[PDB]
Image (tube, coloured by chain):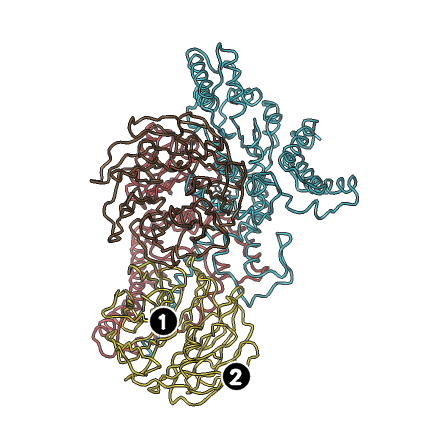
Chain colours: A red, B brown, C yellow, D cyan
Amino acid sequence: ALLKSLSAERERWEKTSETFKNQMSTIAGDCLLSAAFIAYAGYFDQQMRQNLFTTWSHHLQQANIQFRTDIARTEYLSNADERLRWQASSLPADDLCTENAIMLKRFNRYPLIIDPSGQATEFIMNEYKDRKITRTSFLDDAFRKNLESALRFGNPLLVQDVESYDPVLNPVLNREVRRTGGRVLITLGDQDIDLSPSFVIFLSTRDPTVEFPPDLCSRVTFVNFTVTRSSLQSQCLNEVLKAERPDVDEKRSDLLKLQGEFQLRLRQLEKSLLQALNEVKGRILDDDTIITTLENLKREAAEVTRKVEETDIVMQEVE
Amino acid sequence: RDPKEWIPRPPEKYALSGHRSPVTRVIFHPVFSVMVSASEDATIKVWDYETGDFERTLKGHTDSVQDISFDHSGKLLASCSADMTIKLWDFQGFECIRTMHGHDHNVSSVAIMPNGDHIVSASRDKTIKMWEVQTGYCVKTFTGHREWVRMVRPNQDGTLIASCSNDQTVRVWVVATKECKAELREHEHVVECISWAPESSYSSISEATPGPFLLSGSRDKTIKMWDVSTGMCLMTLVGHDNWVRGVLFHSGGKFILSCADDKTLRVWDYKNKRCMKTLNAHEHFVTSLDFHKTAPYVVTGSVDQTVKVWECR
Amino acid sequence: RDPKEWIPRPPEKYALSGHRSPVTRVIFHPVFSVMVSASEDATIKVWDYETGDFERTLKGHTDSVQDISFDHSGKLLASCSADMTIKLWDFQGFECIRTMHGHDHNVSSVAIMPNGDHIVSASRDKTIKMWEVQTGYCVKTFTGHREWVRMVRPNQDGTLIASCSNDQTVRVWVVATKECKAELREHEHVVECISWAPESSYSSISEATPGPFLLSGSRDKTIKMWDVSTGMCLMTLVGHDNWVRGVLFHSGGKFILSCADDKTLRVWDYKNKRCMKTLNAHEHFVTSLDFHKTAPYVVTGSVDQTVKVWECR
Amino acid sequence: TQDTQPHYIYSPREMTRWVRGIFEALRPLETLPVEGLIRIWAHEALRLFQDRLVEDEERRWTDENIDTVALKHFPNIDREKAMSRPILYSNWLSKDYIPVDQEELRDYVKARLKVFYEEELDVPLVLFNEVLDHVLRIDRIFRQPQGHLLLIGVSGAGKTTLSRFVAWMNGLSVYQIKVHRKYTGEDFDEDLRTVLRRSGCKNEKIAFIMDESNVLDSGFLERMNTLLANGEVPGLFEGDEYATLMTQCKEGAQKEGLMLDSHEELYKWFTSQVIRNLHVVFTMNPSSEGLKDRAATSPALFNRCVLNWFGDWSTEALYQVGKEFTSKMDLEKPNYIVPDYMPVVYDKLPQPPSHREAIVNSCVFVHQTLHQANARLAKRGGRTMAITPRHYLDFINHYANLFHEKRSELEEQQMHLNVGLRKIKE
Ligand SMILES: Nc1ncnc2c1ncn2[C@@H]1O[C@H](COP(=O)(O)OP(=O)(O)O)[C@@H](O)[C@H]1O
């Protein structure tokens, strides 16, 4: 019974073991494309982002460097759990905002978000809620004191109104940091301020048509929250369902949440089973914890079987 | 031979290595034959120069130890590292005794006067703190520099201390009057190393041209002899191709030993104004040197994580 | 004391724990006061033997690493595992350098002869490949073994290469002419480990009964020393009660250190051929040992997930 | 000529600078052959007639002209010994101004940067031939009295960092005005009087680093014009500040030993000290209109200042920085097949290129095609945002981070899977 239950995992584990040798060779090209996208394609819109990615892919193909061409440039960088957390924290479900959240999570220079819609501001507020984030503006009188407090205390900060840029942030954004042994010290204006390692700053914009000086363009990373055809189509379709077919819309939302939870629990199954069978520390035939793993596997086989009817009812609702 | 004519000769006697980081300072032990080195990995390794073998490793610091110094008896060792700590060690047990805190920034050097009851230290907080060894307390703090102080050093009787700092000045401070005696500024670039005249060289400098005489080497590839009393330089010695990091006298009181960042060790005679020998020390920058009072041995630390022993012939 | 009589004494100096899996091979660094250990959980942990503190781990392998090797420069790390690959690591950045392929079976031994230009690799595929350092490409290939090659070790001059396999023979080869200069069939069981006689041991073996000489330890209840000039067994060491696993020579070239599966660290001699000190090491079987050339430290590697260091007096 | 670029003005001032450059290059050297004389003539010629140029074609024309003029006027000469590729001169490796080679210069600069990271700026730097040439040019300007600089280059190219490194290593003290909002001409004049007091009365070297973005009014540029041209700003010290300056200047003259009274000779000595001690480095971005505007509104910036055109990083610079940053990571495939189309974007690429060479060339292509895409988007009609070498450094750092992260994840998952299959086989 154990082997019959675990053959379903063996038949794919051996396949992935064989695939790993090929997957070792695509790492360089795939990471090259991913890094170029995540450091270069921030300000541009969807069409220009796709044009740049196509140009880079064509050059890698012409240079005989193998890259995984059957993966999504956002699925390669994002995990399912962090995608679920972002979708919970008011992020739009389109690939553009998913890439923007990828760049916000994996930033190297401090990002400059441009959200005319105001979605990125509330997304950042919801995401950095456990850490005490504080909203402030460059035009606010209590900006220097708030920046000093955030720098001293290691609290994330979001600065709106970057059009009126206040140039005291040049050492912070350039990371001109003096290391006092193990201590970290940075100058700011007329004072030397202890820079805590767990400090991040986001600069915000509510106007797409703002011209920035090249020094700021070098110092910050642009994250453009534009609007795309697929996103607007999905938003309008959801609003039409909410207004006209409320029962259909609410059961669609409930089924989408249930499908997400079911996929999360299936991934939890896979991780738990792999880590439990990894650390048996002996013969699997001579233990009862293996029987506990078998019971977990059969219960989760039952739930992954019951996911199919949810898929069917989602299919009828979407058609 | 005669300690008057002790001069190192190529090649080195031993090539001692084992540090994981560049070596900052090397000094000799006065009583028992120990050469102890300080490095950038918080390891103060103890070596034996008589037979050229590794002896022991003393790890008490958490960041790069900068300078080490002894007392009149040689049984007490002090060290200073980038983690704002001064540590006093013994050699009867090779055990750390008392840690010393109170400086704001990187402590740059420490020194113990021959009376042995007090220890001075210069740091990056532009101050020299007057400590005491008995209870680990700061007696008072010298103040008056403008920038980071490179190292501090007392005279023979422990009443005049001098210090070199990044502001192109070398200030002599009186331990008695607690006031700067004669601050002189003549080097164009940062001064890095200083030294004092020994008891058996006043006649030598007087013939080459009382006292007291103060040495000072800087990063402008020059070495200057200064008289503390007159507040004026005697002369400027040139010849180094890069930054000078250490200057020291000789047992006979007639020679000047100095190492620089030009990957050479140079020993000079100041009577006839010129360099007399240029010894290729390392393959990288030479950080420091020390000269044995009673033995013909010279130790020179460096950045390439090696300590070399030269025999004075 | 003199290093000619450095035997480990009970109890152990440091008991280092932290390995999840059996430990395979343990070696000492040439210049740094640090040492690495290879275990069965696809990790290479590094420990400071002087103070017994954990430094870091090196995880870049996907299967159990079997053997590790240094060079004379002490900057490049070799490691062979069961994942059909060998991996190079640098000691200044502590990162992977090159992933190499070419063996379709488990690789059990790896070493670098002191020129620092190429690598040997003994694997289960009845062959030994010659791979390069600066490029990572196969240039030459040994052929002639017909069973699993267990351990490969290059001679100190590097002109002679020695390999022992599971076919009751220890076939030594020539690196240049690609020819097995001495093959013999006298072992009764599988030979496990080999070692090379130093220059100090050359004269000792010559006066015991010129050179070079060789030693092999085999599962046939016998440990014997080989000679390449005559191609004959010069002596046989008997007295261990179980399967032998690791054996090595002393720094002074006069003593012998061995470990077996009876949880013993039995030191012997060639003049008298009896064990003057049998010492218990672990609770489980023992894999590998290492004695420092310039330090009195013996490290014990065993499958009991624990590595111990012993002090020689 | 001046119609090609506004700063392309030539005068016998450059011949005088050439003559004196050769003079202090031959002053303490005391033993030189004609090969060395031609070499220093060529080096000063390059430093005076090539720094202000914009286009690599013009730079190649200058190099060819130096070679052919030296050949024409100096027959039966050793061309290879006289002129070569690096032609670098330095005074860091020796007390005298002697020629140096790139390898030893790079080793020394890397060691000095290791020393420099601890003291002021703990930001890593990558070395290449343009950086070596730039630090030597900035050092050469900083050594001479009244040495002022005008660095023309895109933002994020490292102008102020190279200036800070050279200033630190030459004993200069770096000063920046720390501009912010509501920063007015009164605050600028207070900063100017503080730096002038420090440079004249206190007798210290100051590298007054300032930027075009730090200019907020025409009074800023007027004061900078007067200070650059004359070494003094009349009307800056008024009221009790004039009396304070006179007291401090008399104290400084007493401290340095010179006996001074009255006010006229004291102020003249203060002007001489400011001339001998204060260095101004001005950094802006290249512009067709802005450069002409600065030439009109401040002739001192184009007369009394030595102009260096850093510009954008070249493809050779991008290739070398990418290769040096991607050297610690594993990138070599032994079974690599070179494509026969050979898309190459960096000339003098090794042939056949290996895998790491090919992908660093690919990174250079990625930067180049972003340049082209930005130009196309600007020409279409939409708004554009300037691209900087900071973006290339960000891209290469993201490449390193993503490579290490993905490799670690893949190896961990493969190891877990292998142990799981071994246990199920058991
Ligand atoms: N040669 C180089 N190698 C590596 N990094 C560099 C180099 N030059 C510049 N940088 C990086 O680029 C940044 C440039 O900052 P800065 O000099 O203030 O910009 P600007 O050149 O516009 O003044 C620095 O923070 C530095 O980290």
Q: Chain of mark 2?
A: C
Can you say whether D171 is above or below B5 in the image? above
Residue C21 % position (x, y): 30, 70
Q: Is residue A12 visible?
A: no
Q: CA distance from mark 2 to mark 1?
A: 29 Å
The answer to the question of whether label 2 and label 1 lie on touching residues, with beta carbons closer than 8 A, is no
What's the residue type where badge 2 is placed?
Answer: Lys
Q: Secondary structure at mark 1?
A: strand
> Front-most of B230 and B188?
B230
What's the residue type where badge 1 is placed?
Answer: Arg
Residue D33 % position (x, y): 70, 42
Q: Is residue D379 visible?
A: yes
> Front-most of C15 and C233?
C233
Q: Chain of mark 1?
A: C
- Which label belongs to residue C25? 1
Residue C235 % position (x, y): 38, 86
Residue B187 % position (x, y): 47, 31
* Residue placed under numbered mark 2 in the picture: C181
